Image 1 (tube, protein in one colour):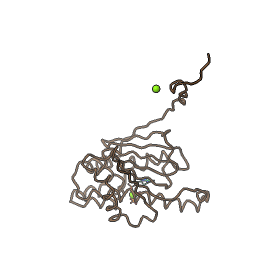
Image 2 (cartoon, protein in one colour):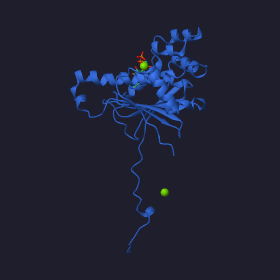
Image 3 (cartoon, helix red, strand yellow):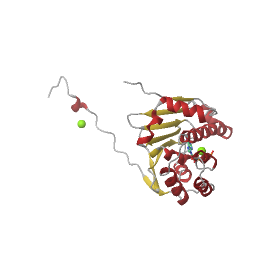
Image 4 (cartoon, helix red, strand yellow):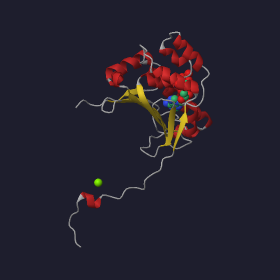
Length: 232
Ligand SMILES: Nc1ncnc2c1ncn2[C@@H]1O[C@H](COP(=O)(O)CP(=O)(O)OP(=O)(O)O)[C@@H](O)[C@H]1O
Ligand SMILES: [Mg+2]
Ligand SMILES: [Mg+2]
């Protein structure tokens, strides 16, 4: 049956087989859940320090590449730059912190980002009760949860050399999920995606982001760059 030209629907290629992603749900350790509730539902004047804690974590993960090379030189063969990118998306109201540090395995996500008690958590909650500045979070070993000063939901996508790529996600409320992530491979590192609360959109503005990186994160020790989407 001769054809000289086909329409797009006709030559659309069949989909790749659908992938399964395994999902597991976990409760936050009790004091972690308590802290998150405190962080979310209390007014703090100096919420901007969230970005200091996430940059700090990225800088730690990047220093680990430098040091893991002493026990495993193969990391020296990576051509990836050691760096951080800050990516505001005003369309989606997200602020993403991307690094090319060592990343986390599945068990790292579960054990490091919620099910294990930090020994400073109770002390920190008491300090906050007695009126401490929220900036003190960074000294009590629970700085990641400062994301929820500004974010209603946090997704962390991560890939470590020793595991597959995973997504951790929580809207607080007492639990989080970890799921195998078969989507856009991110390569080694971690991306924290902050789904900002409606009153916190200043952290999508490039002037605001530059201001708080200069104020609080001037010794990262790696290049950080801010991607600014061109105004249409
Ligand atoms: N960008 C990232 N890359 C890799 N691991 C990360 C990460 N962000 C967070 N983590 C993991 O999450 C853990 C919890 O981080 P935080 O709540 O900041 C306490 P910490 O950073 O371990 O101590 P510190 O903040 O006192 O230096 C880290 O120890 C690390 O294992
Ligand atoms: Mg169709
Ligand atoms: Mg930290």
